[PDB]
Length: 52
Ligand SMILES: [Fe+3]
Image (cartoon, rainbow, N blue to C red; front, side, top):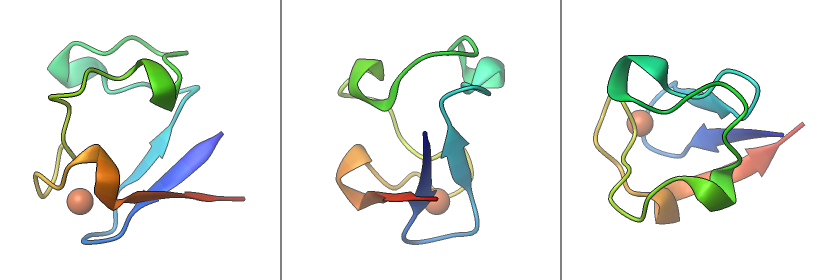
């Protein structure tokens, strides 16, 4: 699944992960640490919303 950061143009795609910050491809959003934030703008998980 894919989730948009409400606050910038970033999209978290579970099939991409966030590898530059230590999150492997295939990591589900539910499994991101509670201290994970958007790699571009620092918004928390509460500021992401599922998109198609
Ligand atoms: Fe962002």
